Amino acid sequence: GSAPKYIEHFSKFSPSPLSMKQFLDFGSACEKTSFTFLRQELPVRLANIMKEINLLPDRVLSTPSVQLVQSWYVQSLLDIMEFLDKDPEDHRTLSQFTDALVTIRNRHNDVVPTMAQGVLEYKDTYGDDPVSNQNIQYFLDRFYLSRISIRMLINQHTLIFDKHIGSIDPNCNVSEVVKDAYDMAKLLCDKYYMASPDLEIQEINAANSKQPIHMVYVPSHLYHMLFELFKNAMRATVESHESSLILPPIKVMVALGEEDLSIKMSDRGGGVPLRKIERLFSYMYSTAPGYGLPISRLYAKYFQGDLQLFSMEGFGTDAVIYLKALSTDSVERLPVYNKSA
Ligand SMILES: CC(C)c1ccc(COc2ccc(CC(=O)NCCN)cc2Cl)cc1
Ligand SMILES: CN(C(=O)c1ccc(O)cc1O)c1ccc(C(N)=O)cc1
Ligand SMILES: [Cl-]
């Protein structure tokens, strides 16, 4: 077959990063333009990460988990090829493309636990030394960020072409998503432990005091990040206080600046020594017989944000999500192939 040829052809192109603005217009332009963009751009993004997978050393590349994930990418690339010569004016071309995108999305659903098996296998077969750790961290950050960007493109297409513009809410109420993610974490926390800390939210709209804080964002991404952080802050708070009676609340601040929308989650869960912070973000060190924090950080990075942890051992932990306030500064952050090693 031609998969290596295709990979070589499309890995010559740079992925084209889109802004929120571009994303919002695509969901007014129309389906034909999404189709002609995506039938080029998906092969480009697939091929760029496939090329990088093929550069892994043989002792990683040869493992069943990587071979299995590589086989999903090959089929998904081939599924998209079928449409390169098809006619955009034919509505059967367009419906079949949508169908093809849903199968591709479904096919890749189990990538994270599959890659996690790969990490486990490597720790036991070759070890968990600091250089292994950096190479795993380097690869998976790029792999998972690539995969977030491909799921975004596919989600935008399948949701728009069946107020919100697919996965984008142009009037996202940040405090409402905070309360949703808290309410869900509390539910699980109450079930597993006999208790759950309360929530306090404070907003700081610097320029418009007392105006509720809204942004253009992908609320499912924001939920994913906040949910992960709530789980961590609830587990720490409950477990560090199980001989105490009082349960300090979790305090969230939502700050809107000129360019940053910042969400701090402050807990009193006893904290982590500085030495152990790096490990919480490490796929390798956080793999035991992917993970929430490292992948939540990629969601934040995806539109030029970040996710930082600062703890005070003996007291508690601050987690901050940094987002861009402005749709104009919210541009896909994409890993690009070439330079290497
Ligand atoms: C996520 C899974 C599948 C996974 C598991 C393990 C790895 C680890 O990959 C390593 C490990 C060590 C080195 C040092 C070295 O030898 N450098 C030169 C390269 N030979 C390089 C790489 Cl790319 C990546 C991804
Ligand atoms: C102590 N501890 C923290 O202080 C802490 C870590 C991360 C976080 O977002 C919030 C925290 O309180 C903490 C550490 C690890 C987990 C975990 N991954 O299960 C949870 C909590
Ligand atoms: Cl789109």
Image: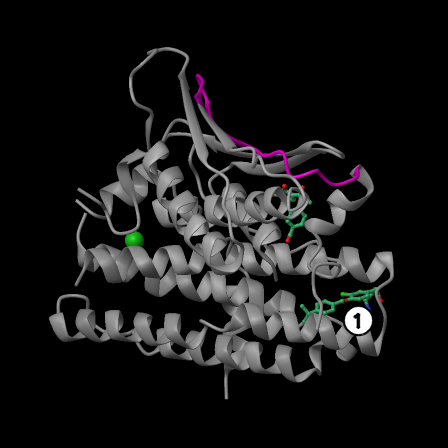
Residue 149 drawn above or below residue 305? below
How many residues crowd mark 1 within 10 Å: few (<14), some (14–19), many (20+)?
A: some
Which residue is drawn at the image coordinates 70% and 73% (left, top)? 289
Which residue is at a point 12% across and 70% down the rendered structure image?
91
Is 58 positioned to the left or the right of 306 in the image? right
Q: Which is more toward the observer, 328 or 38?
A: 328
Residue 80 pos. (x, y %)? 36, 73
Vertical order, 106 against 10 (above or below): below
Q: Quadrant of residue 229?
A: top right
Can the viewer see residue 4? no
Q: Can see residue 203?
A: yes
Tell me, yes or no, whether the highlighted magenta stretch contains residue 260.
yes
Q: Which of the 4 image quarters holds residue 145?
A: bottom right
Residue 13 in the image, given as x and y percentages of width and height:
50, 57
> From which residue to which does the magenta span run?
255-273
Give the percent coordinates (x, y) of residue 271: 71, 38
From the image, tell me which residue sits under label 1. Answer: 123
Quadrant for the C terminus, please.
bottom right
